[PDB]
Amino acid sequence: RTRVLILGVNGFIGNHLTERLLREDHYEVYGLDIGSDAISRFLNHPHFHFVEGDISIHSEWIEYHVKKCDVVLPLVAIATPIEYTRNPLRVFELDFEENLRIIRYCVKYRKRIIFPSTSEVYGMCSDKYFDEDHSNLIVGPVNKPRWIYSVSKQLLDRVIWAYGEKEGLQFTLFRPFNWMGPRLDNLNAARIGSSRAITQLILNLVEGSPIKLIGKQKRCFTDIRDGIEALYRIIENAGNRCDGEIINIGNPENEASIEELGEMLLASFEKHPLRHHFPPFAGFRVEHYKPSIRNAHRCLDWEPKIDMQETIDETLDFFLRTVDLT
């Protein structure tokens, strides 16, 4: 069966992607990380193999699994805004330099690489719907440090594209738009996956802190149920329709501003069985951004199905029931 190397498996995507692949009968999953607390349910599974490791520290050990496997999924990256501006150099070394090494192992051993790009690469693009193949990418002056993340991920994309063009690297790039659902990534985990904005809000509701509002700008959210299904089809690569493709993965109908998202969580929150176990709501303390999903349609015959309310209730519910009250 197909050997899937998941680098940074101890989190949101690794958990859902693993559960999925394992439901099928033709995948062998090699999940590499420094801890397994988040995928313990899979440790004793016959087709799962935890691999002790760290992409900043290990060189050889990782190169070896790239060669030993068929498809590689690099999920390790610092994807926390405050950090873009706080420890930018560390964000560049991990996100850019260390992943570049993995990309290179992939071209060297002729392996398929499914790389998580970012929805942030579009920047201040005026298109109502961001198009992987046509939208221009707009960022601010170099003196506006917040963009180092976006531009870094973008340069990587370009380098992957270059290897695909001049050296036969087989690949697929995916750009997830605010994925959410059960088993969210810890706010400070350097693993790509779950929307930090919504997990910060749930955190607010859980800790009794207020929801801070810049809350104007609107965003698209995607249920992990719909998102992981898409990712899974990219691994399937039916008819190889994904080779050389860049695919946005989001539900363009779930639009909502920070304040609207918050309002939605509050509602589901106030009606939740465990509501009494959480502090009273602290209150609210004072452009476009939609993805085009044509490529997803084309390459995957994919279309988001879960209704937004359903996603809101479930993500919150699972979170509340998982909270360690003691």
Image (cartoon, helix red, strand yellow):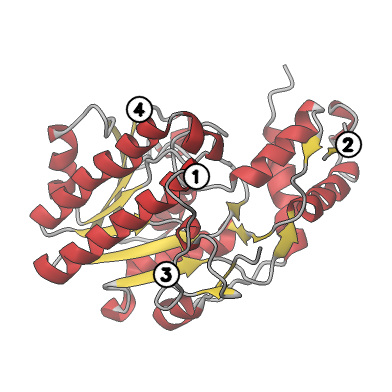
* Classed neighbour count for the residue bearing mark 1: other residues with Cα under 10 Å, few (<14), some (14–19), many (≥20): few
Given the image, on which type of amino acid does mark 4 rest?
A: Ile
Q: Which residue corresponds to the image point at 14% horizontal and 41% vertical from the top-left? A: 63
Left/right placement of residue 103 relative to residue 279 reads left
Check disc 4 and report the residue beneath it: 34
- The C terminus, quarter of image: top right
Instruction: Give the mark nearer the N terminus: 1 vs 4.
Output: 4
Mark 1 lies on a secondary structure that is loop
Q: Assign a secondary structure to mark 2.
A: loop
Which quadrant holds the N terminus?
bottom left
Considering only order in the chain, which callout, 3 or 2, is on the residue closer to the N terminus?
Answer: 3
The residue that mark 2 highlights is 283
Residue type pointed to by label 1: Lys
Q: Position of residue 66 (x, y in %)?
A: 18, 47
| Drawn side of residue 25 relative to residue 60, left or right | right
Q: What is the distance, in whole Å, between disc 2 and disc 3 at their CAs? A: 37 Å
For label 1, the residue is: 144
Q: Nearer the viewer, residue 94 or 264?
A: 94
The picture places residue 5, in percent across and down from the top left corner, at: 27, 48
Relative to 241, residue 316 above or below: above
Mark 2 vs mark 3: in front: 2
The residue that label 3 is drawn on is 247
Asked if the residue at tag 2 contacts the one at tag 4, i.e. Cβ–Cβ closer than 8 Å, the answer is: no
Q: Nearer the viewer, mark 1 or mark 2?
A: 1
Q: Earlier in the sequence, mark 3 or mark 1?
A: 1
The answer to whether residue 274 shows anywhere in this view is yes
Residue sitting at 46 percent across and 43 percent down? 143
